[PDB]
Image (cartoon, coloured by chain):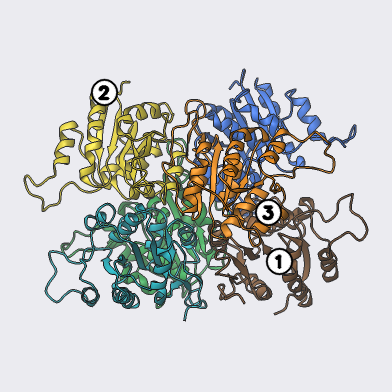
Chain colours: A orange, B blue, C green, D yellow, E brown, F cyan
Amino acid sequence: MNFAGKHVGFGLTGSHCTYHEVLPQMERLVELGAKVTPFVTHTVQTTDTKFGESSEWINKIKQITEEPIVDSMVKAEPFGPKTPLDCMVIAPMTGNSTSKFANAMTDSPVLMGAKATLRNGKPVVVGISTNDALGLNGINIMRLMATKNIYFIPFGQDNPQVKPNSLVARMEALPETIEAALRGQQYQPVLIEKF
Amino acid sequence: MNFAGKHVGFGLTGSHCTYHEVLPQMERLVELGAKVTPFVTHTVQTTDTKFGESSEWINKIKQITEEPIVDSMVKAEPFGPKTPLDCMVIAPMTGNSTSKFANAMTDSPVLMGAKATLRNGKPVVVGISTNDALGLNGINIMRLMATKNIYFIPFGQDNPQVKPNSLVARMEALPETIEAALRGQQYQPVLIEKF
Amino acid sequence: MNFAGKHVGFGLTGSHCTYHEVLPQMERLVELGAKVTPFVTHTVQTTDTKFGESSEWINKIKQITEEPIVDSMVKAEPFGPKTPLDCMVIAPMTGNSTSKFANAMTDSPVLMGAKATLRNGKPVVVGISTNDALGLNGINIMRLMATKNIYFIPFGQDNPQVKPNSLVARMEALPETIEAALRGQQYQPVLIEKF
Amino acid sequence: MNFAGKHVGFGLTGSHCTYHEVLPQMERLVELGAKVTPFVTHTVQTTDTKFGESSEWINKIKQITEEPIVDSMVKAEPFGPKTPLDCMVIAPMTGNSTSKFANAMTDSPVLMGAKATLRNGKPVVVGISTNDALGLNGINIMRLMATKNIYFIPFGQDNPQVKPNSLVARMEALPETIEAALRGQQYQPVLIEKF
Amino acid sequence: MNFAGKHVGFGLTGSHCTYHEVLPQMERLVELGAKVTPFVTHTVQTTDTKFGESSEWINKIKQITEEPIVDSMVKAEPFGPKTPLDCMVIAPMTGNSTSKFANAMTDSPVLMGAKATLRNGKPVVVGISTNDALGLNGINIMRLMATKNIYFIPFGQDNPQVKPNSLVARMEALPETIEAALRGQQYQPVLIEKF
Amino acid sequence: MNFAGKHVGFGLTGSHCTYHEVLPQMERLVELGAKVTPFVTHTVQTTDTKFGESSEWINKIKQITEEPIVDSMVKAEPFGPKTPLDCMVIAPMTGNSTSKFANAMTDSPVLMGAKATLRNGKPVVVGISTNDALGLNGINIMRLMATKNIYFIPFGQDNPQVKPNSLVARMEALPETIEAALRGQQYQPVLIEKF
């Protein structure tokens, strides 16, 4: 398993404090040789922002990869025609992002990265994480699972008694999922037992 | 009919000046003993906002219930794991909110309240109010009507000659709809003749 | 209201013994001057069939109109290119027929009549009658209601306490629905109170 | 766990030789006290049929339960208004039956049993078994999983390397799934590891 | 072809620098006699904005038509009950706008113009322009194409080898598409060969 | 372009007399070296059938290929686990077959061949031919176009003035479409101008 020479986009959705489960996977991809471009859902700074106010997570991304963080539509768009990715990852993918992605809405820098990658016939790999995955998001998920060029990090119910509709990916399986996606395949078993 | 001990969330969507049809129903729930938490789609104040600039509707909510208005994602999220509602109401539910809700988008404090309530298997009760309900919103509405744990305040065409696609709930039926939802039932007749 | 010169197809779906609610409407159309062609879902005779074995309903159709009953795909198909209808009615339209029609299946003579009429941009008017209309059929119904050239005989819940998902058309409104459909309009109010 | 006094319908879909995985579960329900009515997708005899020609599976059903096999639309229909079930099971539910059920088609005695049970607000429990469950059937499955009164026998991928889209229920979990469905609940974990 | 007396709304979605393909068509409508109201997706000025900072495109709209630019929900809403359009155009319609429109979301001034026009039974004409039109947006597009009162400027693949999912309208066909829409018809051929 | 060693299934749907447009393409595949198995939607003989009663089309298939015609579910099923195809073609694919296929119904030998091929991750290539393709079938078509392992023989409107919703494949492009499908690609341009 070797991503030398590969340009992988890594988009993060949802609350900043849930990224401790995926940043170690971003770090593994860089260690396996990938050039990793981070994508995020909002601007990382306002005119207003002061010296050491930036949350830890941004600093952590900057310690993993020197690729500029894509945090605007303008910055995301060239990943279609100019600087194409070999693969785009979205992890964690929240319920809101899942239903936007599944319904062809593309109103965040992350979803624009995904759209720009799909434009070229290249793979998008998603790590779901939502408590409505077996409820209102079920059709969205299964729509994506069946769609050309879209692949899922293996997933399962994380707490069936307390959150019976919740599905969450095994983030440790991310590199393997990318490796199979780059060959045009869904990595298997896609359904796993979480913890 | 008695809601003593019950924690009901009451989310408002759409223009602030359409809430005169639902605030009297919020007031009835409090009078019937419910603890009512209001949810709204945007922040109720900016840094900028001055003394008596706040619109009447906010003041009116504050006269009905002392529960803090949930006007942010941060404030809405604990209604899943920490402070669960027995029922969430969304009334009025606009066409835009209807199609976001039906498609699993959860990008407002109101929709997060609904998602957090559905996470726990608890009921959400909606009062539709849109002029495209029998047009592009029809599938969204019927999707929701058939979905586990989602119930509709009885509704009908409010002006068939002038707005032939428009459906609006009879807001006076809200408490009865909550009472049936808390038993796992859709209150009937769900189709009524408006005015 | 005058259908002189108009060629209206009248398809019947579901059990033969439910047609007592629509045959009087077929008779009114003929009395208002329409040329009415009946369409049915299966062959009206097998090689096997004997003299007075044919059910009353067939005889009743034959007393209303002398147009040959279209009971096969071969017989239905020319209503596209050769003998086009000005309007096709499907009443009663069962839940099974509703979900086939809504999903573009066309495997009965009735649905082929509808397809052949839609091919030409001409109206199809449906009278629903199913106990799952507000359940699994809801999306199918609302899909059809929003689709070009498809119109609904006004309908409502026929027994909300006992069959809460059931919607049935007011068959007496059929001619009026045809009249509005021929002008490109849905007759209003489309939602009525049944009995 | 006790089904004394309960009338459970048990519909079988697909090839006759796949019923060896569900007949032992039909037998457990009878042993736990249920009155079990079998439903099947076609007529069990033609005029033509001879003495010992009937396949073993029919004989096996007849050894488990003395309730007449419902093998026609006429026989299935009274399970709505006259002889209502407390629960309807469909197991195995093939891909074809899954997509008919999910799309509101009701053109077999089994699907009519399910429709007649849903008419009354009563539960239907399904055991999927199709090699396209994570492909074209994915949306159908997730639609059903989210729909009022429909519940799934826990399921999983039965051979991810060879049939990566295949999901099959753990049929041994059927009684437990019925028990939770009768209380209005999906039995959990709904996602399991097959064999 | 003459639009004298006609009030046509012209909404623009997506990047400001893609409007050079549609402004000449806005200009033709005014030259053919239409009163053209522009609709845009965001506010055209902030408190902050300075003298000659406004992008060329705004100035260009202002040279074509003196109707105030509708750039807010408040400004768009009266096009339902007070100042109804005879037709609303959305061109270019981006992938994001397409999937919002198709899913009944109405959270921009442009989509509110479209909703307000559909409320009245009046036509909306769309010019698609997205690189995912034959991918994730395909169902949205075909949903709209089949929906009452919605019509498409003829379109085709603009670069099948490089962007195989991309569909873009022939903007030169816009007036003809409006003319047919005003008669209740889709202008044909709707599928063309781009450049 | 060489199909030596390749096992291609060729399913025919719709009226027997429309196969003159695809049998020459079946013949080209055999001439290019493919082993071609025909699939059809019904049994090719009844007990009843007499000597020279069989329609010309059957004889014509038998002159092109000696592979037994798969005309039953029993015969189609082994193309999953025992005798897998490298590709399955469905041409012509009627509107009825399109909406069954798109909705995961698998109730004909042709659709079972397609299901059995998709089970293995292998390509299915479809040639649409229906007068409702841009109407009620639009979502079905676009669903299939976006689905893993499904590819379309290039298609277009065959008579936009007379049948404005009609799409039909250019059957001459079938081999090229198979060649690209076997590499995991949709052959381009997929949208063409018919005749």
**Amino acid identity at mark 1:** Asp
The residue beneath circle 1 is E86
Residue under the image location 31 percent in, 21 percent down: D2
Instruction: Identify the chain of the residue marked 3, using the numbered disc in the image.
Output: A
Q: Nearer the viewer, mark 2 or mark 1?
A: 2
- Classify mark 2: helix, strand or loop: loop
Q: Nearer the viewer, mark 3 or mark 1?
A: 3
Tell me the element at label 1: loop
Q: Nearer the viewer, residue A180 or D59?
A: A180
Mark 3 and mark 1, same subunit? no
Q: Is residue C152 visible?
A: yes
> Badge 3 local density, few (<14 within 10 Å), some, or many (20+)?
many
What whole-number distance in Å separates the C-alpha atoms at marks 2 and 1? 68 Å
Do the residues marked 2 and 3 share a common chain? no
* Label ID, residue A189: none
Q: Is residue A45 above or below residue A131?
A: below
Q: Are marks 2 and 1 on the same chain?
A: no
| Res C30 seen here | no
Q: Amino acid at mark 2?
A: Leu
Label annotation for residue D32: 2
Q: Which mark is residue A76?
A: 3
Amino acid residing under circle 3: Ala
